Image (spheres, grey):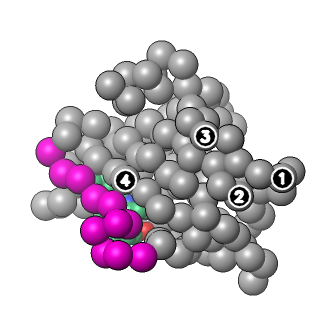
Amino acid sequence: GAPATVTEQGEDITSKKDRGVLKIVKRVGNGEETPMIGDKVYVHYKGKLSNGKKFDSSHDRNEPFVFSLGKGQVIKAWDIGVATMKKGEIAHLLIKPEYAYGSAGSLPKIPSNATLFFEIELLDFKGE
Ligand SMILES: COc1cc2cc(c1OC)OC[C@@H](CO)OC/C=C/[C@H](O)[C@@H](C)OC(=O)[C@@H]1CCCCN1C(=O)[C@H]2C1CCCCC1
C-alpha cells in the first residue's frame, strides 16, 4: 500500500537523516515558492495510524485544515513536511513516533510509539 511505497521510495526530509519523516510527491504543484515559518497554510489531508486502527480527514469536517507553519500547532513531521510543498502539490508522509506523538502517545486516540501516515494536498499559503 501507499505507506509501504513510502518506506521503499520516499525521500528522508529530516535534518538528522534518521528516516523519521519520509516523503513521496504524488502530484506536482505550481511555482517555485514553498511556505515559510509563520505562513498561514491551507490543506486537505487523510491520516491514519500505519496499523489502520484510527483514520482522520479534513473532509470529515467539510472544510480545509488551516494552521500556521512552524508555530506550535501540528506534530513536528508536519512543520517539516508541509514546508517542502508547493501550491497544489499532493504528497505522502510516513512518520516515526519521535516526529509525531512519541513514547507518550496521545491516549486513547494515539498509542505509544505510533507510526503515522498522511496524504496531504497543499491548497494555499499566505504570509502572517
Ligand atoms: C491527537 O489529536 C488529534 C490528532 C489528529 C486529529 C485530531 C486530533 O484531535 C485533536 O482531530 C481532528 C481535529 C479536531 O477535530 O484536529 C486537527 C488538527 C489537530 C492538531 O493539528 C494536531 C493534534 O494534529 C496533528 O498535528 C496531526 C497533523 C494535522 C492533522 C491532524 N493530525 C493528527 O495527528 C490526527 C491523527 C488522528 C488519528 C490518525 C492519525 C492522525
Q: Residue flagged by tag 2: what amino acid is it?
A: Lys
Question: From the viewer's perspective, is 66 left or right of 13?
Answer: left
Query: Mark 4 and mark 1: span between their CA atoms?
Result: 24 Å
Query: Are discs 1 and 2 less than 8 Å apart at CB?
Result: yes
Q: Earlier in the sequence, mark 4 or mark 3?
A: 3
Query: Are discs 3 and 2 less than 8 Å apart at CB?
Result: no
Query: Mark 2 and mark 4: span between their CA atoms?
Result: 18 Å
Q: Earlier in the sequence, mark 1 or mark 2?
A: 1
Label drawn at residue 87: 2
Mark 4, residue position: 46
Q: Residue furthest top?
A: 8
Q: Residue flagged by tag 4: what amino acid is it?
A: Lys
Mark 3, residue position: 27
Residue at disc 1, secondary structure = loop
In the rendered image, residue 54 lying in the magenta stretch gets the answer yes
Mark 1, residue position: 31
Q: Residue flagged by tag 1: what amino acid is it?
A: Gly
Give the x, y percent position of residue 31. 83, 52
Q: Which residues are magenta?
A: 53-63
Residue at disc 3, secondary structure = strand
Q: Residue at x 60, y 40 (%)?
A: 27
Question: From the viewer's perspective, is 126 left or right of 47?
Answer: right
Q: Earlier in the sequence, mark 3 or mark 2?
A: 3
The quarter of the picture where residue 40 lies is: bottom right
Q: Residue at x 33, y 39 (%)?
A: 115
Residue 23 vs residue 99, the one in the foreground:
23
- Image quadrant occupied by the N terminus: top left
Q: Relative to 48, is 5 above or below?
A: above
Residue 122 vs residue 67, the one in the foreground:
122
Q: Residue furthest right?
A: 32
